[PDB]
Amino acid sequence: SSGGGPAVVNNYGDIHTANYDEFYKGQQRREAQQQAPILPVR
Amino acid sequence: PAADAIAKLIIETTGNLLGYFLLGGFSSAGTIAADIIMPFLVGTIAAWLQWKNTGRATELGWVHYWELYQQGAETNSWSLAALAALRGGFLVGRSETV
């Protein structure tokens, strides 16, 4: 039942429903977290 | 620059040194000099302006960031406009809503 359908699509990962907008926004948020404190105030 | 401009450091200091020399200061230390050490104090006399934003401190409270050095768009204009330089410096780290 589970093996060979949506339950294995979940194992496949982001093949079905998955959008680019929030993924790009999350990557930008992670980079902003990394680089914002070290950016100068000037 | 109003205290240690290069024109001052050359002309006024060499004149004071020549006056001291003609009075005999270098022959014996008795003579009282008149500003013969100006080139030794470049960038030390009234070279800064520090302003603490009382309203910002009141709004922020006990725990706060202390101070920030701000360089203006024109590097040698704060002496011309002290107030404008301080306001331009305080333009930076303010409350922001977008």
Image (cartoon, rainbow, N blue to C red):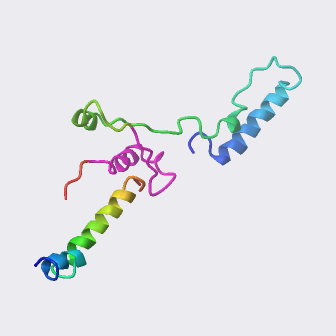
Horizontal arrangement in the rendering, residue B52 relative to residue B27 (left or right)? left
Considering only vertical position in the picture, is B74 above or below A8? Answer: above
Q: Is residue B86 above or below residue B44?
A: below
Residue B5, picture quadrant: top right
Between residue B9 and residue A8, name the one nearer to us: A8
- Residue at left 24%, top 48%? B95
Tell me if residue A13 can be seen: no
Q: Main secondary structure of the magenta part?
A: loop
Above or below — where is A17 with respect to B74?
A: below
Q: Residue at x 37, y 36 (%)?
A: B66
Confirm whether residue B39 shows in the render.
yes
Q: Residue furthest right?
A: B27
Q: Which residues are magenta?
A: B67-94
> Does B72 appear in magenta?
yes
B50 or B98: which is nearer to us?
B98
Identify which residue is drawn at 72% across, 38% down: B13
Q: Is residue B33 left or right of residue A37?
A: right
Screen quadrant of the C terminus of chain A: bottom left
Q: Give how far across and how far down residue B94 sits, in percent.
A: 28, 48
Residue at figure coordinates x 27%, y 72% from the top left: A24
Residue B42 image-quadrant placement: top right
Q: Position of residue B6 (x, y in %)?
A: 66, 47
Q: Residue B87: percent from the left, percent from the top?
A: 34, 47
The question of residue B83 being in magenta is answered with: yes
